[PDB]
C-alpha cells in the first residue's frame, strides 16, 4: 500500500486545469501568498548554502530535492543532497499541506550536483551528475561527465547506479541533469539534460550547420538577416566554454527494480531546439512539454511540445510568452530581440494552466523575476503568448532571488486551483539562500 | 513494528550524557552551530506567525509541535498547530539528521494554544488548551480553561479527547500547558501545566502563606527580612491578572488507546515552588526534573527535582544555574535578586548534561537570551551551579529572539554527544519569526 495523496486530491493532479475557450487567459490571476506547511528545510547555520530545487508530482506522490554546501554557495568541493517523498492532504478546514513521509539527507563521499527528481511508480527517481572538477573544468574534460540514476523508495531507503557514460554520453565533454523535474511516461521516466559535445563527434556533426531563430512577439530584430543567421548559428558555441557546442538533449530510463536499466538519449535537431541549457520534462493530462531555460539570447519563457514513441522523444515549435521574460546579461537582457551568442539567464519554468477544448495550450503559471539584467523582484502571474495578469509580489521592495519552479493542481473537494512556486530567496542570519515554496490560489475576475 | 532511531543512536537518548566528578562542569562547551536537516517548517507568507515550540524525544522517536497564526503574532482570532513525529538517522558520512515520518497541519473548528508534546509508546501525545477569549479575559473567566489530550499516532492519524475541566481543574480560572515538552513515565504521560487559581477555592487557601525566597549566588538582597517575606508572599498574586494566584501544577494522564483516561493533577506546595509559569518535564536517566520559566523575580534557570509515586509526583528544592539568566523587566531584570511581583521573563530551558556518579546534577546545556530586559542575542553553552562556559552565537549582531528549548543526545557509536536547541529567531520577509532548530556538539577544552 504505497503512499497516495488524500481523496480530496484524486483526479486533480497533473491534469489540464482550466479549459476555457471564451475568457482571456489573463483574466485569471494569482491570489496573495497562502500560508501552508513549509516542507523545504532552511539552512541551519549562518553560512549554509541550499540551492538547485527540483520537484515533480504524480497522481499519487510528489518528490523534492536540493543541494546543500556547508561553507557557502561558492565552495565546490563536496556537498550532499536532501530528498523528500510525500503526499498532499487537507486539514479539517480544508487547508492543504505537503506531507513528506520520507525525509533524508543523502550524503556520502560522492558529490552529486544539479540533480532532478520525478515521481515514478516505485518511488522518487533522481538523476544526478557526480563531479570532481568545476563546470568550467569539466567542459574541458574530454571525458563525459559521470552520471548516476538513483531512487528513494517508499521505504525511505535509497539506491543508485552509475550510468555507463563512456558510451551513453560518448560524444560529450560535459553532461548534467536539467535540474528541473522529470516525468514518468509509459513505464519510463524522462529527464532533461544538457552539456558539452566533443567537437567533430558524430553527434556534433549532425548539428553542425543546423540553427534556429525564434523571435519576439512585437519586436522584429533589426540587424540584417545575414547578421541574425550567422549569430544564431554560433549561439550554440558561446565563448563561455570555449566554443564548445552546448547541446540540449533528453534521456529516458526504464522504471524498474533495476536503477539505470535501458537508458536512451535523444538529441533533437538544433533546427528546432535552442542552445542547450537546464530544462524540465512536464506532463499535463495527455500532453508533454520540455521546458528550456533562457540561457541563450531568447528571453521569453519557452515550452517545446514533446511526444514519445519507443524510448525516444520529439520536440516541436515552442509555445512562447513575451510577458514571461527573465533577467539576463547584455546583449541578452530581458528585452533582447536579436539573436546573439551569450550564456546567462536563470531557471524559471512556466506551468501549463489553461487550454482549449482542442487541448492546445494557452495560459501558464510560474514565477518570473522582474529585472532587465540582475536577478531581482520575484513575480507570480498568469501568462498568455503576449501579456501578463495582475501579479503577486514576494516583496514590494527590491529583492534578491534565483531559480523558481512552479506546479499547479486542484482540490476537487473544494473546487479550487492552487499553484506551487518553489523560489530561491535571499536570506539573512542563516545562509545565502532559503528555498521557500510559495503557494497561490488561481482566482479569476467575473 | 514501530518507527525508531538508527542503531547508531540506540542507548544515547534520554540518559545521563556525562558522568564526571572532578572535571569542571564548565570545561565543556558548545561547538560552532552545525549544518543539519532543518526539520522545522518556516513561514511561507509575509505575515505568517510561527511560535511556541515544543519538543520531547523518547528512546524510540521524537515529537515536535508549534503554533501558526495567519495574520501575524498579535492577532488572537484563530490558529492551527503543526505536528511532526520522527526518528534520528545517520548518513554514510555519519552525519545526523532528524528524519520526520509524519508531518501534518492540524487545523479545524477549534483554537489550540500553548500546547506541549511528549513521546509516548503510542505515538506523540499532545495537551492543548482550547481558547475562545484572550489570556487576560480568561484569567477573569470564573470557569476553567477548556483542554484536550490528543495524540498523533505512528500511523499518521491524530485523535484527541476533551478533558472534563469543570471537575479536573475545578479550582482554576485559567490553565494552560507549560508549552515545554512533557515526559512519559511509568505508563503515564506527564505535563507541566500552569494558570490562575479560583480565589477562595480549596486549592487556593492551601497555598495561603506558602512561598519561597530564592536568592542569587554572589549578590545578596538588601531589603528587610520583613519587606522580603511580603514581596515573595505577593509574587503569587501579581497585578497583571487581577491579583489572582498564578499557580504551578503537574498533570499525569494514563497512556492507552483511550485518550484522557484517568488524568490526575498535582499542585505542588509553594513552600518549594515559585509563581506558576510555563514549564517542562525532563527525564534524564533515572532522574525526573521540572523546568520553570522565570516569569517572576527569580532570574536563574530552575530545575526542580521531580520524583514520582503512582499518578502524583513530588517536587524538591531546585538546582539553580545562576549564570543562566533570562531577560526580564525592572525590577525583575536579568540581574534581579530581591523578591518582587512581576509576570515577565521568557522560556529558555536547561537540559541535564553533566552528572556525578551519585546521580546528582552538575551541569546543563541550554540557550539563554543574553540581555538584561529586552529579548536579544541568543547564546548556547554549558552551565554549572554558578557560571557559564564558552558561548556559541546565532550572530554577533543584535538579534531579536524569544523561546528556546534544548535536548541533548549521544551517538553511542562514535560516542559523541550532541545538543539540539530549538529557538524562535528574528526573521525577515517571511513572518515575524522563524523557528530554527540549532545543533551543536559538546566539546571539552582539552
Ligand atoms: C503599499 O501597499 C501594499 O500592497 C500589498 C499588496 S498585496 C501583496 C503583494 O505584493 O502581492 C501580497 C503578498 O502575498 C505580500 N507578500 C508576502 C510575502 O506575503 C506582499 C507584501 O505584503 C508586499 O510586498 C508589502 O511589502 O503584498 C500589501 O497589501 C501590503 O501589505 C501593502 O502595504
Ligand atoms: C564575529 O566574528 C567571527 O566569529 C566566529 C565565532 S564562531 C560562531 C559563533 O558566534 O559562535 C559560530 C556560529 O555557529 C555562527 N553562526 C551561525 C549561525 O552559523 C557565528 C557567526 O557565523 C558569527 O558570529 C558571524 O555573525 O560564529 C568565528 O571566530 C569567525 O572566524 C569570526 O570571524
Ligand atoms: C552544473 C552547474 O554548475 N550548474 C549551475 C548553472 C550553470 O552554471 C548554468 O546552467 C550554465 O550551464 O547555473 C547556476 C546558476 O545559478 O545560474 C547554478 C547551477 O549550480
Ligand atoms: C497562554 C499565553 O497567552 N501564553 C503566552 C505567554 C504568557 O503570557 C506567559 O506565560 C504569562 O504572561 O507569554 C508569551 C510570551 O512571549 O511571553 C507567549 C505565550 O503566547
Image (cartoon, coloured by chain):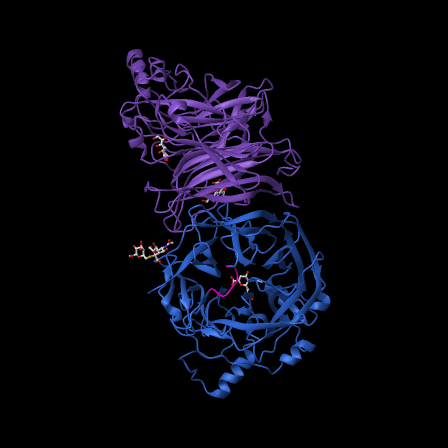
Chain colours: A blue, B purple
Q: Is residue A212 left or right of residue B210?
A: right
Q: Is residue A106 left or right of residue A329?
A: right
Residue A17 pos. (x, y %)? 47, 64
Q: Which residue is nearer to you in this view: B23 or A293?
A: A293
Q: Is residue A111 above or below residue B97?
A: below
Q: Is residue A432 above or below residue B268?
A: below
Q: Is residue A114 left or right of residue A422?
A: right
Q: Which residue is nearer to you in this view: B132 or A32?
A: B132
What residue lies at 61% left-to-right and 78% top-to-bottom? A269
Residue A254 pos. (x, y %)? 68, 63
User: In which quadrant of the rendered image does the N terminus of chain B lie?
Assistant: top right
Q: Is residue B352 visible?
A: no
Q: Which residue is nearer to you in this view: B291 or B445?
A: B291
Q: Which residues are magenta?
A: A12-17
Q: Is residue A398 magenta?
A: no
Question: What count of labels does the image hold?
Answer: 0
Q: Is residue A200 above or below residue B88?
A: below
Location of residue A262 (image quadrant): bottom right
The picture quadrant for ligand 3 comes to bottom right
Q: Which residue is nearer to you in this view: B196 or A17?
A: A17
Residue B215 pos. (x, y %)? 38, 18
Instruction: Please tell me whether the stretch drawn in magenta is mainly helix, strand or loop.
Output: loop
User: In which quadrant of the rendered image does the C terminus of chain B lie?
Assistant: top right
Q: Is residue A14 magenta?
A: yes
What residue lies at 39% left-to-right and 65% top-to-bottom? A370
Q: Is residue A383 visible?
A: yes
Location of residue A377 (image quadrant): bottom left
What residue lies at 37% left-to-right and 31% top-to-bottom? B327
Location of residue B378 (image quadrant): top left
Residue B232 pos. (x, y %)? 33, 17
Amino acid at each position: 500500500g504505497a503512499p497516495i495523496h488524500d481523496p480530496d486530491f484524486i483526479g486533480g493532479i497533473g491534469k489540464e486545469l482550466i479549459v476555457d475557450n471564451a475568457s482571456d487567459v489573463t483574466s485569471f490571476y494569482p491570489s496573495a501568498f497562502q500560508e501552508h506547511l513549509n516542507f523545504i528545510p532552511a539552512p541551519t547555520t549562518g553560512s549554509g548554502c541550499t540551492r538547485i530545487p527540483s520537484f515533480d508530482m504524480s497522481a499519487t506522490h510528489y518528490c523534492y530535492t536540493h543541494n546543500v554546501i556547508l561553507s557557502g554557495c561558492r565552495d565546490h568541493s563536496h556537498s550532499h543532497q536532501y530528498l523528500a517523498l510525500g503526499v498532499l492532504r487537507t486539514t479539517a478546514t480544508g487547508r492543504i499541506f505537503f506531507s513528506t513521509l520520507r525525509s533524508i539527507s543523502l550524503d556520502d563521499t560522492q558529490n552529486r550536483k544539479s540533480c532532478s527528481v520525478s515521481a515514478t511508480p516505485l518511488g522518487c527517481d533522481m538523476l544526478c551528475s557526480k563531479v570532481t572538477e568545476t563546470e568550467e573544468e569539466d567542459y574541458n574534460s574530454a571525458v563525459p561527465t559521470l552520471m548516476a540514476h538513483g531512487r528513494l523508495g517508499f521505504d525511505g531507503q535509497y539506491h543508485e547506479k552509475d550510468l555507463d557514460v563512456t558510451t551513453l554520453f560518448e560524444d560529450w565533454v560535459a553532461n548534467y541533469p536539467g535540474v528541473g523535474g522529470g516525468s514518468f511516461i509509459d513505464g519510463r521516466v524522462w529527464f532533461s539534460v544538457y552539456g558539452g559535445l566533443k567537437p567533430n563527434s558524430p553527434s556534433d556533426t549532425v548539428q553542425e550547420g543546423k540553427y534556429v531563430i525564434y523571435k519576439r512577439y512585437n519586436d522584429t530584430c533589426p540587424d540584417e538577416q545575414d547578421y541574425q543567421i550567422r549569430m544564431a548559428k554560433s549561439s550554440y558555441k558561446p565563448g563561455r566554454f570555449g566554443g564548445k557546442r552546448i547541446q540540449q538533449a533528453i534521456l529516458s530510463i526504464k522504471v524498474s527494480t533495476s536503477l539505470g536499466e535501458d537508458p536512451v538519449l535523444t538529441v533533437p535537431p538544433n533546427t528546432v531546439t535552442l542552445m542547450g541549457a537546464e530544462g524540465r520534462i512536464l506532463t499535463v493530462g495527455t500532453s508533454h512539454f520540455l521546458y528550456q531555460r533562457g540561457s541563450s539570447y531568447f528571453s521569453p519563457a519557452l515550452l517545446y511540445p514533446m511526444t514519445v514513441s519507443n524510448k525516444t522523444a520529439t520536440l516541436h515549435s515552442p509555445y512562447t510568452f513575451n510577458a514571461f521574460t527573465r533577467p539576463g546579461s547584455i546583449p541578452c537582457q530581458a528585452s533582447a530581440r536579436c539573436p546573439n551568442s551569450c550564456v546567462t539567464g536563470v531557471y524559471t519554468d512556466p506551468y501549463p494552466l489553461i487550454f482549449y477544448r482542442n487541448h492546445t495550450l494557452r495560459g501558464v503559471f510560474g514565477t518570473m523575476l522582474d529585472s532587465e539584467q540582475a536577478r531581482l523582484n520575484p513575480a507570480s502571474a498568469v501568462f498568455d503568448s503576449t501579456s501578463r495578469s495582475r501579479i503577486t509580489r514576494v516583496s514590494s521592495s527590491s529583492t534578491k532571488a534565483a531559480y523558481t519552479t512552479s506546479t499547479c493542481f486542484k482540490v476537487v473537494k473544494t473546487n479550487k486551483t492552487y499553484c506551487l512556486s518553489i523560489a530561491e530567496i535571499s536570506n539573512t542570519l542563516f545562509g545565502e539562500f532559503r528555498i521557500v515554496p510559495l503557494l497561490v490560489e488561481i482566482l479569476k475576475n467575473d
